[PDB]
Length: 153
Ligand SMILES: O=C(Cc1cc(C2CC2)c(-n2cc(CNC(=O)c3ccc4cc(F)ccc4n3)nn2)c(C2CC2)c1)NC1(C(=O)O)CCCCC1
Image 1 (cartoon, protein in one colour):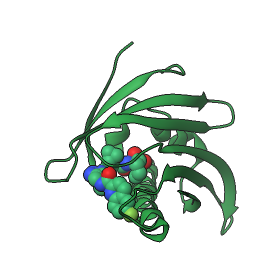
Image 2 (cartoon, protein in one colour):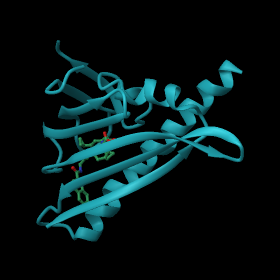
Image 3 (cartoon, helix red, strand yellow):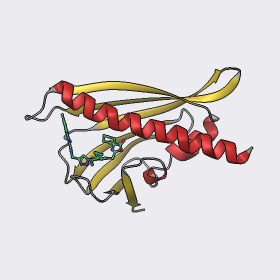
């Protein structure tokens, strides 16, 4: 079985600023709070990033492949292909879109994933685990880019 879900986040910063952060396949640690470091050899499709998680977690690293980087429509797609975690066949897509909330331009982020349900867990538990982490990441992306936006004011 799999869990497939989509999360949406409203960000009070312009798309060009949010995308400048999200597009850095080589620098996820700039807003993903559970990631420490990241190294990419050679940002083209097929690029492989080796990700160091923060110390004190059950896993320590992830290996992920760049499946999509569309700089015109603002789509980033990745797939996890290794590491000392339990997540199997994880892939995700995030896209950014301009929107106007309260008369001010902002950015809508849409992030979708598909992942296997491990044999020892329920599908509900798998969805909850992944959705909570992505929500954490999207909340942090909003915090980071809204802060950059304020610092530019
Ligand atoms: O943000 C991150 C960073 C990131 C990446 C990883 C592992 C290396 C993939 C981890 N992790 C995972 C683990 C060990 N548990 C699992 O494997 C795991 C797998 C299936 C599970 C199913 C369940 F029912 C309950 C618990 C489960 N537990 N130890 N550390 C973390 C820790 C939990 C906070 C954070 N990753 C994502 C991103 O968008 O980059 C967003 C979340 C989804 C992956 C992509």
